Image (cartoon, rainbow over all chains, first blue to last red; front, side, top):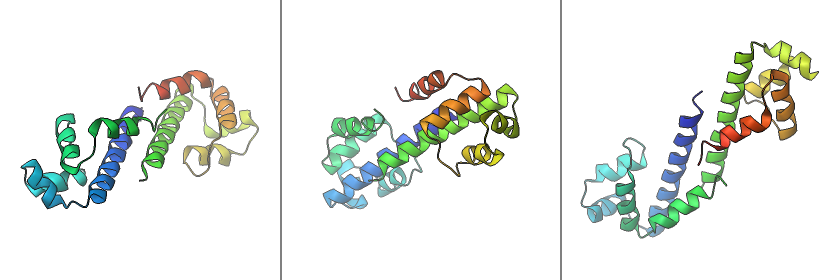
Length: 82
Length: 82
């Protein structure tokens, strides 16, 4: 079946949901996050819009750029499928 | 965020995907499954179309009706989020 990818896609989308919540809470614009990352704003916007794939390395940096602990965010996400 | 429900919905849809695979593999029509369950065909069709919610009791019976071990199916589903 397509179960494996179906579940992967939702967990990935939930992670994006959490990251958007975190950036918004931090009061940081996409343009500002991109500046901190030393990347074009398109990097941040495409990441948030799911038009490019985030790897775990980019993810760690994205988190640090907004001020949120990447290990803690992952732990919280994982806690959602006990 | 909406993360918790986002993840729940995907796991539920993946379970339906697996159940459809199982009924199809068993060579059993919806009408035939319903007869075995002693329920209207609409029960089976709405279950498969996600137009009604399956509870764990109905799920066990649905599985037995198609010949597949409900405990094993759940285990397989859970294995997908290690």
